[PDB]
Amino acid sequence: VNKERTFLAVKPDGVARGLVGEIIARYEKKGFVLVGLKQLVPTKDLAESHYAEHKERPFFGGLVSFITSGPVVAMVFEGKGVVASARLMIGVTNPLASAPGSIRGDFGVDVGRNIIHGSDSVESANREIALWFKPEELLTEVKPNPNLYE
Amino acid sequence: VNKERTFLAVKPDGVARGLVGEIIARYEKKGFVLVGLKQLVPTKDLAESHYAEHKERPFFGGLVSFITSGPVVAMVFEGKGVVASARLMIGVTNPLASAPGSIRGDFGVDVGRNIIHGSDSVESANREIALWFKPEELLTEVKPNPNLYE
Amino acid sequence: VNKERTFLAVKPDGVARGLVGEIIARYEKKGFVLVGLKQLVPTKDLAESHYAEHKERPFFGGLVSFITSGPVVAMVFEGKGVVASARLMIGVTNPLASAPGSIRGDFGVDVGRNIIHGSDSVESANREIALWFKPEELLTEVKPNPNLYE
Amino acid sequence: VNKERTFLAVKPDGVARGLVGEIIARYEKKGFVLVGLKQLVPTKDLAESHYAEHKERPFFGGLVSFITSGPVVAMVFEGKGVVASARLMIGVTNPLASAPGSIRGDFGVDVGRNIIHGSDSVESANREIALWFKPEELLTEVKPNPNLYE
Amino acid sequence: VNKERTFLAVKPDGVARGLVGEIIARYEKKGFVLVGLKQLVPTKDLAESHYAEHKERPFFGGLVSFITSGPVVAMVFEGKGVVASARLMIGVTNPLASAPGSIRGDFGVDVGRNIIHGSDSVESANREIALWFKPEELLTEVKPNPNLYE
Amino acid sequence: VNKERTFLAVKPDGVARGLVGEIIARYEKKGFVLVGLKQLVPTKDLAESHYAEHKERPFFGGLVSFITSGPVVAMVFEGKGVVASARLMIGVTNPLASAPGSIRGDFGVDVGRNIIHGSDSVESANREIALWFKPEELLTEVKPNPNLYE
């Protein structure tokens, strides 16, 4: 249960705006454990797979183009209720409606330039992690601060 | 649309408590662009005009007295949905009910000493900006970070 | 009214995670005044009294054991609406459901390791303060920033 | 003596990089009092006057061009030893040689894009303030935190 | 050796300026362990004893008066080289000459209102701790983060 | 010249203490560009190669053991004078002697647990980058903020 994992990606706008360290620090302070981490420029295929769920929609081409427009920092965090907790820390789709204190609430203004991606569910988290990372790239032995869990 | 503007004023208590830089930084981090900025001690007339909407109420005299009691930092910010977004960043009238993460939620305790003023609408924003600033004092050419807007 | 007081305790996990200064700073920035402060390792009796309200429940033994497992930083803050305001700053019982910007929302993950204690009411605040502090240990003459209250 | 004043200007690169609030906060935290403040796009004449001391040098044309390339946030701070203290807070001409903790040490990399200007002496501070601000724009009645001066 | 201790006191100006949490956080982040902590209003006798080394000097009366003018937060920190390390974190006697990054460099302007006290040596640290704290008030069992010491 | 690169590694203690995001943010704020990034648990061979320069010394076995004791966040930053600048931001070998404002000055206490590694020269930076990263893992097209370089 405390072994739950989520996939987060600091999108090109977030990387370009120098928000990588600020975003990672928020998750480390919360107590989640960094299990995978690497910077990369996504290829079209990985992009199309990541957004496959929208492949029938019109905006799908825009999503693929943007995520491949520059480097992305992909990461996997582990902890209890991480998937839902990470979404709460990010905010809502529209940054302008995101509450102050959340990532998008503090730094974003446009839905199209919303800084970060967080899996919306455990199953999507599982698919995305396996999509973005090779098993060799993920920590197998995870140990959080002992003052974090009862 | 991304040319929307709002008027913000760091009231005398906020200036006296050394919260000017902290408040400006929150808006700059969000991505809004500083279009006008100056410190001044409001005269009675500008004050009465700013709060004209309350001129029939009893507390109106108290509002005018306080805002003229010391320096005020007036500023104009530009961005998409800035008017509503800036209000969300400020919090609610009563600082004690404002959520942690918002300006009044983080620093205020009294309705009467609530640190900052934000226009409540585009039309009030337009009236206030034209009230507090001469056109010469506002940037005509505004350019935000290109990683902010799609 | 502006003489209202609340009891806060940074529990063993919070002390062990180096969150004492971060927690105090949040309350000082808000404008509340530190009226009592000391680090101690609670004895079983003080613990049982603090959680007396749960003495009939099963988890009561767990509460007493944990709070006595290490040092605790007890403090008393004074200000208008401090009791409710301090609870809002802390968040909800479950850290995972606490909103970003609140103490538990920013730093906690487990109900059992939720970092801090805040009185839930004026009467409980009164009982706890008198329980944890000798009158000699509390400031009698309190003076907040004059820019805080109208 | 505690009435000493200095002129600071957040140059175009600093304004464009969203460092205005961060810079003001550093001076407010230190205890200096904001006496003048306004955003403006310097004209060529004000620029040439500001850098008149270099009018015989080759790089002088570059200085004038850059400072007039965009908005600048000009400010005047008051306090004991403000002139030398503000320079120490800024760092050295070359940002790369500026120590971590100073403005240029924390945020700059190029001598040509060094973020901020601080008067190098009382006499230059006097000339610059009178150059950049009309007397009407400066606070006459200055009152710092009483816990700042003995 | 890693059991070395120092005495720190947040003086009345520091407490009044809301700098208590900020100061404690700096020491916790560094890795030092809080061993004693309490707020108090020093009596004349404790004051005269604390500054006994200056009892023959003229300014001695001023030191005693100020430290007894309001609450003080006394604390004892433990760690390797804590005594010298804590002084380096504080800065020099004159806040204006203290480097940015240090406590006095970041927040002070006057020698007379220099925010904090740090023992200048192990022997003075020993005398001050035994002067300000009863043994019952100090942690006997100290355990720092295991990732701090080799 | 503005294409200079350095290799930084957040060692196991730094990763375990949740300092990864804090360290990256310091470099991003400075203006350096993240060119490579990944978390890994170094193997003995990579370790021995990284510290090959000390292979004749006694402490060499201790260095290899520690760096392989847990995950490490390796990164490559690009910018003008990055190699020397990054060392200045880190501090000196002994954290206790590192000045407040630097990474080791703010967070470390023991030479053996000094949080981070920074190449000491361009040639060592070149050897380390080629040692720790495959060319495919480094950005070829680097573009910093245009407000950073003249």
Image (cartoon, coloured by chain):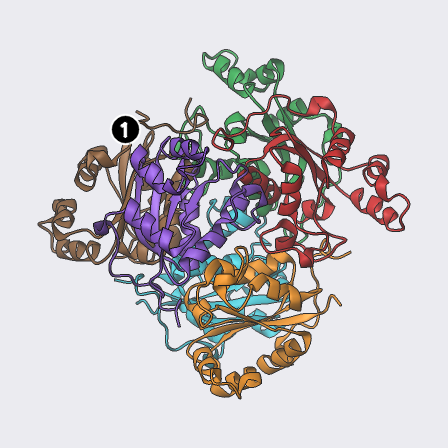
Chain colours: A cyan, B green, C brown, D red, E purple, F orange
Figure check: B69 above or below C129: above
User: Which residue occupies 20% across, 57% down?
Assistant: C66
Mark 1: few/some/many CA within 10 Å (<14, 14-19, 20+)? few
Q: Is residue B120 above or below residue C40?
A: above
Q: Position of residue B17 (x, y in %)?
A: 50, 32
Seen from this angle, which residue lies furthest left? C56
Residue B107: x, y in percent?
44, 36
Does residue F131 appear in this view? Answer: yes
Tag 1: residue type? Answer: Thr
Is B148 above or below relative to F52?
A: above
For the residue labelled by badge 1, is the local secondary structure a helix, a strand or a loop? loop
- Of residues E117 and C68, the one nearer the viewer is E117
Left or right placement of residue B55 versus residue F66 in this view: right
Quadrant in which residue B92 is drawn: top left
Residue bearing mark 1: C140
- Please state the horizontal and vertical placement of residue B94, each as a whole percent of the image: 41, 29
Q: Residue at x 24, y 58 (%)?
A: E140
Q: Nearer the viewer, residue D45 or E57?
A: E57
Which residue: 64% across, 21% down? D140
